[PDB]
Length: 45
Image (cartoon, rainbow, N blue to C red):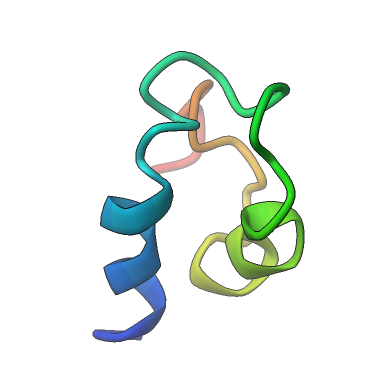
């Protein structure tokens, strides 16, 4: 997902702290780019 993770940088603002603040777009995107739904926890990478 070269383009999938691309958003990660566009939404990084979320994982930059957690996600519960701007998790509007990634709400579904993070579901694609990421399957662990733990971009902040990153406990599955």
